[PDB]
Image: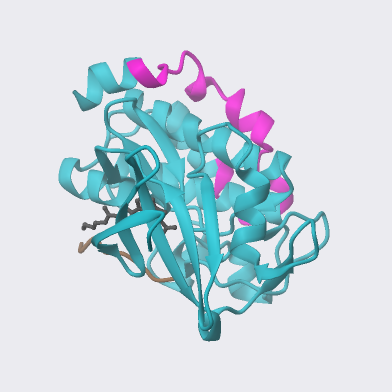
Amino acid sequence: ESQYQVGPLLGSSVYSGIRVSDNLPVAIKHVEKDRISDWGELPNGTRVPMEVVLLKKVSSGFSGVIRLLDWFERPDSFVLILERPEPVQDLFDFITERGALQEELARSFFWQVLEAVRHCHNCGVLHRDIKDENILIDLNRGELKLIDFGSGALLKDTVYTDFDGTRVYSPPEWIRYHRYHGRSAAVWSLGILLYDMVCGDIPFEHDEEIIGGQVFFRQRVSSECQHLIRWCLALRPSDRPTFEEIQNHPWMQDVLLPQETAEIHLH
Amino acid sequence: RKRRRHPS
Ligand SMILES: NCCCNC(=O)c1ccc(-c2cccc3sc(C(N)=O)cc23)s1
């Protein structure tokens, strides 16, 4: 209240903020205790929402994730203080405004998202809600940042039987069997994301389409990029590429640096 | 088609 000046709302509950300390732009996320499904313990065994546990674990220094700067407990809620780049726009609004992205730009963005998801995995965190809505663009730096770990979990190599993520980005094995593994599920969602970037919208709206495993390109997409998307969207999890095989794919070579991407595509 | 957000 006194440590930060609260501004107006952004999206639903996240508000614009300024840190009184040094006038740093922040985002102030409120989470209702009554609406929290999954709880964790901190390294000092304090009972907090899983979101805070996952945010603390990924808040190393690699800035492909929106870092948690601070948090507060209140009687009926938790307040998360997150970094706020300015100017910013989420990748969903960016794609709506600009339509199907050029392959060069899609390569830069998809690469940065891959580096951010690998970072999460390296820190033992599975995001479980990778989509254009959960990616912020710093328009000056040309840096993408992952947000909203509220559907996340600790990474494990054993099967998941729960999911609170976006259904249209969820894989066939979830729709059919209520069963998935983190990595192969994440690769599926990244297939949806890449299609979404180069085609201007997600390929599937209905369960029938998700489990169908037919990918129709509504926009001109190179054969190399079509192959990567088809491979990520393989029906059988074991047939999906590893993060290694994605980043070694011919389509992913000669990526633009963030600043190159800002200069050429965002300025 | 109609492009839209999808909730979590
Ligand atoms: N059609 C216009 C919609 C406007 N909407 C927006 O611009 C934004 C909404 C919220 C934003 C945001 C900015 C900085 C940090 C974090 S963390 C976080 C989260 N949910 O965890 C969200 C954010 S950006």
Q: In this view, does A167 lie to the left or right of A124?
A: left
Q: From the top left corner, tell me how far across and down residue A191 is, in percent.
A: 50, 46
Quadrant for the N terminus of chain A in the image? bottom left
Give the vertical position of A175 relative to A44 (above or below).
below
Residue at 20% x, 62% y is: B1
As drawn, A209 above or below A123 = below
Q: Tally the marks.
A: 0
Give A251 or A18, whichever is nearer the viewer. A18
- Chain B drawing hue: brown
Q: Which residue is drawn at 33% across and 27% down?
A: A105
Chain appearing in cyan on the rendered image: A
Q: Quadrant of residue A153?
A: bottom right
Q: What colouring method underlies this structural image?
A: by chain
| Rendered location of residue A44, percent (x, y) | 80, 59
Residue range in magenta is: A231-259
Foreground residue among A263 and A40: A40
Residue situated furthest bottom in the rendering: A34
Q: In which quarter of the image is residue A256?
A: top left
Closer to the camera, A63 or A45? Answer: A45
